[PDB]
Amino acid sequence: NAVESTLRRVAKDLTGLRQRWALVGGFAVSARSEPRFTRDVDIVVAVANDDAAESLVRQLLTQQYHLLASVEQDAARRLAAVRLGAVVVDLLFASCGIEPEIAEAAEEIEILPDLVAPVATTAHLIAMKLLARSDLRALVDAASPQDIQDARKAIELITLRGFHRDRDLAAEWTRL
Image 1 (cartoon, rainbow, N blue to C red):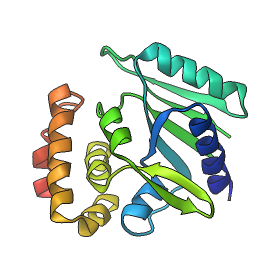
Image 2: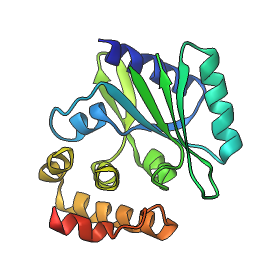
Image 3: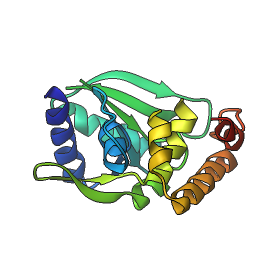
């Protein structure tokens, strides 16, 4: 209940600030395949640089959220994600490296009554789950062949940009 309310507000809010965002969590997956909800809202946001990110989060913290975590990294984009409180919202700026592909690529879908929201493509969802690690099994069982192709591409572009941790993701999959 808190979860749908949280999702509604942040969507209101992100749209409000004309951001390029995309659901990549429980609702997203549920939309692209079968019911796999969580008590977390996972969203990607395409933003220019760390200033953009910082600024966005400041603007959101004037609203009715609190900052529960900054996730940082040694690379050119310091600020990978943040986690906010209202139920928790993870915002991903540069966790996977294809945030802006994902957000261009998302499609608007009506998730709840009179809530349309952009939703990561199945292929992207597959990419991201692999990287985080039956959320995945679901997405794959559900995925069309072209879906699988796009996923491989998405995998590749993550690896190129070198957010692949140090993992052969291509590999990790054929296994699973």
